[PDB]
Length: 340
Ligand SMILES: CC(C)[C@@H](CO)Nc1ccc2ncc(-c3ccc(C#N)cc3)n2n1
Image (cartoon, rainbow, N blue to C red):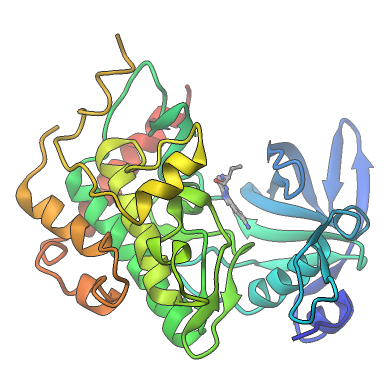
């Protein structure tokens, strides 16, 4: 229900650090973490890339005094209007961030704060996100347009499935914003699920809906239903990620107008051709039945018929998954980053 001050929330975190900003020469520091650059300005959010002891870190900034001013109508239960700030949401995220500890999820290494500014230390996943988006999805650049090899995709999927197992089953947490931006790779190349800003604790394995990224939201959000199965939601979205991994494009949900999108999802059958179908089109390999056999199991409209994560993990498709395929993929991909 209602949550206390930031201090109450962090009151059980055993690695809370007092803020110390200082300047040494031509450099700005946060507690021995040297500021290299800000990786993205999510207007709010904000992730700062730092160095400390020859290691790269990613510290997410958060500002109470900015976040508590940004407030929207949430509409109550009692006809008397309620109102949530983006600081309320952050208090929820803090709780979760405060208890995610898992090798397949991006886990904070410590939290720096004065109880207004918060810098949350994470490892920097040097191979960046799975895919990036600009007009469309790509791996590295966009004059060069390569698709992730199917052997690599298997691992990625298996890995986030292992993330799912922990958050759903050990933690009772639904991610809610499973998305390529949120699937991260290190140089080595492990895959972690990241960003719990829309994630929430489940009640009887369910969430109250409408939250996350529009085109990764499942058909049920568009139904009669007031509550949804958390796992099945996360599964759908991983389904979209897989579809994106196949084609470098989102299924039926191709932006512009959302009515177009929202009218589609619940009603539309997805097109399942071969890799570059959607893609020779804005530019002036193959897929087998089995690849698509498997993706369809993710994107079934009735969530009760939608694959569980258990039956996905031990499906014949991921049976021949080889961690080495991803490792080699990652090692060469990192070599391309060592200057582009
Ligand atoms: C938008 C990008 C700046 C961002 C998210 O896709 N990319 C990256 C790239 C490397 C990396 N290493 C750690 C992190 C990172 C750390 C924390 C969060 C959170 N919450 C989200 C991402 N990240 N995030």
